[PDB]
Image (tube, rainbow, N blue to C red):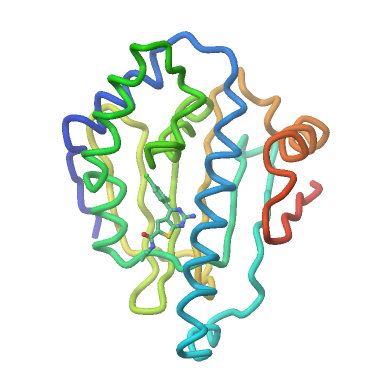
Length: 208
Ligand SMILES: CCNC(=O)c1cc2c(-c3ccc(Cl)cc3Cl)nc(N)nc2s1
């Protein structure tokens, strides 16, 4: 039903660093997630030029941002390529076992956290604002799975019993209690407009 996995030691230490380093510019997390999405839509757009048959589970290639004050969550939803269970398990828990060592040296040599996307591990910035992250993903190959983690060394994968969802990936941030500014419409618009104004796909910010 629920499988529990250990972060590979580097990823866990990176996560630790991200959660523990005092660092005020937290808002860069959104750009990292919006940018993961765009890649994933690129990558599905790519494969449907040799099989316009993969858009059968979707076609509309977009990114939604969904704030919810009462659950204190901000969700970044994309209809991109999605991940299989092994994608999910490898490229969240291992996979850039590499891009992570690079980053953590880079951090000496006055690199600062805001340049995390350059090493392919931007996703982990979500931990600047969230006590818990849930990733709901559905790939053309496979079932629909829920990945989950509040850090602390491990994560879980279970098959998703929730809203079936076409194809793509939903990242749900359960916000830290003092980062509820990222739930707010003007706060979000300012950040999108500042860091992601030229993304190739529509980004719809929902209202509550
Ligand atoms: C099967 C090929 N797809 C992938 O490898 C993907 C990884 C991601 C990711 C992703 C990438 C890196 C990390 Cl550390 C975490 C995630 Cl959720 N996000 C999104 N929104 N879509 C995809 S598709």
